[PDB]
Amino acid sequence: MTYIVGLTGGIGSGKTTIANLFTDLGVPLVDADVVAREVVAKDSPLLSKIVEHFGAQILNRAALRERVFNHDEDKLWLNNLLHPAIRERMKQKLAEQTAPYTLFVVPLLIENKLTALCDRILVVDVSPQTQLARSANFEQIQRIMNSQVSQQERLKWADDVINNDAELAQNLPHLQQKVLELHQFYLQQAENKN
Ligand SMILES: Nc1ncnc2c1ncn2[C@@H]1O[C@H](COP(=O)(O)OP(=O)(O)OP(=O)(O)O)[C@@H](O)[C@H]1O
Ligand SMILES: [Hg+2]
Image 1 (spheres, rainbow, N blue to C red):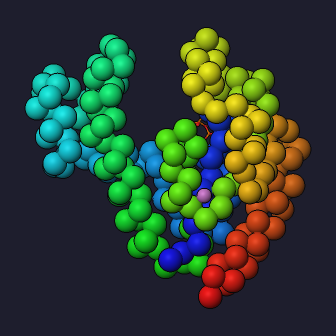
Image 2: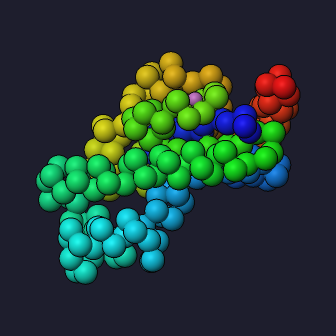
């Protein structure tokens, strides 16, 4: 198996930014939001079950998200259908990779208990004030942050941490360096598996 690095981080923390520096090195990426997308694509068996349950009225993703919001009840139904499907499709894509290591980007890696799927956890860390600043509404982001794990909790889960609080203009070169150092370390971790 590819060595698998789960990348996560709270809303607005810079997961995409960091994932991009790894894909710049030619490292493959399995992205949870992309997979979640594939799973309900136009002609897909999941989609057609969603449509039977909700109506053609919905894929209009905004319409479906809208519907979920009603109460935990339809959300439960959808999660019972999609979460296991997304998980399996993730496993598939990861097992298909033949690079020495793969970056597995998952916004809810901890919260949805997908930590068993990766070898090691990379967190992009920033303060809550940074999350709010970068994500800019203030009200809406805060509720998202309330439903995600705390900074401390995310950090206790992390094997590696890259800090993204400083602005890119000044800190990008140090961010790049830290990614090159992790890159070299992950290749070594992949070799050690053999
Ligand atoms: N260190 C940086 N300095 C200034 N802006 C940054 C920095 N890092 C990322 N950003 C910007 O902050 C925003 C959030 O970054 P990014 O998309 O990488 O985070 P994310 O964790 O993937 O976001 P989300 O989960 O909320 O979609 C983007 O607008 C991005 O361009
Ligand atoms: Hg992991």
